[PDB]
């Protein structure tokens, strides 16, 4: 009752079209988008932001972590 | 007021009034999701990745960079 996932992978790329799944079981997507906006400092005070805006603004956050 | 352009050390806040919908329009979400996959060295190649599991594995990627 309550578990963690101890797993790591380091090979490179991770590019692909992938395969589709039954989208969201426990509204897991909604939990993820909350935690994304907390790790990303680039949120203005008094904004809700759309589901698509979060994705784009997470990429800008990762650009500074990778190569400026 | 209207977001003053000064040097601060605060994010938007955290949680707020949850009001939004999945727009997508053309395919713009998946264009962001592909650009996420480019920066993730934890994905095999052509595996089962829903729009949800991409978010989760991008958080796991950021957990390696933050070390939580």
Image: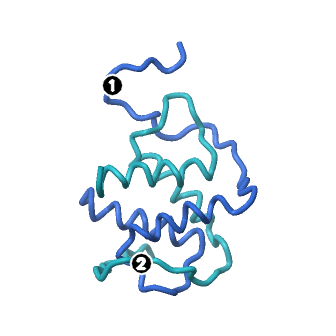
Chain colours: A cyan, B blue
Q: Which residue is mark 2?
A: A14
Of circles 2 and 1, the one toward us is 2
B41 left or right, relative to A28: left
On the picture, is B58 further left or further right than A9?
A: right
Say which quarter of the image contains residue A9. Answer: bottom left
On screen, A6 above or below B15?
Answer: below
Counting from the top left corner in percent of width and height, residue B46 is at 51, 87
Numbered mark located on residue A61 in the image: none
Looking at the image, residue A4 lies above or below residue A30: below
Element type where label 1 sits in the image: loop
Assess whether mark 1 and mark 2 are in contact (beta carbons under 8 angstroms). no
The quadrant of the picture occupied by the C terminus of chain B is: bottom left
Image coordinates for residue A64, horizontal then vertical, percent: 32, 49
Q: Secondary structure at mark 2?
A: loop
Q: Nearest the camera: B43 or B20?
A: B43
Label 1 lies in what chain?
Answer: B
Q: Residues within 10 Å of mark 2 (few under 14, many from 20)?
A: some
Taking the view exactly as shown, the residue that stands out farthest to the top is B1
Question: Residue at position x 63%, y 60% from top?
Answer: B29
Same subunit, tags 2 and 1: no
Residue A23 rendering spot, x and y as whole percentages: 66, 73
Residue at x 34%, y 60% (from the top left corner): B62
Q: Which residue is mark 1?
A: B8
Q: Residue at x 43, y 73 (%)?
A: A2
């Amino acid at each position: 009752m309550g578990h963690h996932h101890h797993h790591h992978s380091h090979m490179g790329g991770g590019k692909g079209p992938a395969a589709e799944e039954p989208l969201s079981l426990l509204d897991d997507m909604n939990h993820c988008y909350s935690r994304l906006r907390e790790l990303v400092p680039g949120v203005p005070r008094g904004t809700q932001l759309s589901q698509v805006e979060i994705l784009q603004r997470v990429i800008d956050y990762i650009l500074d972590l990778q190569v400026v």
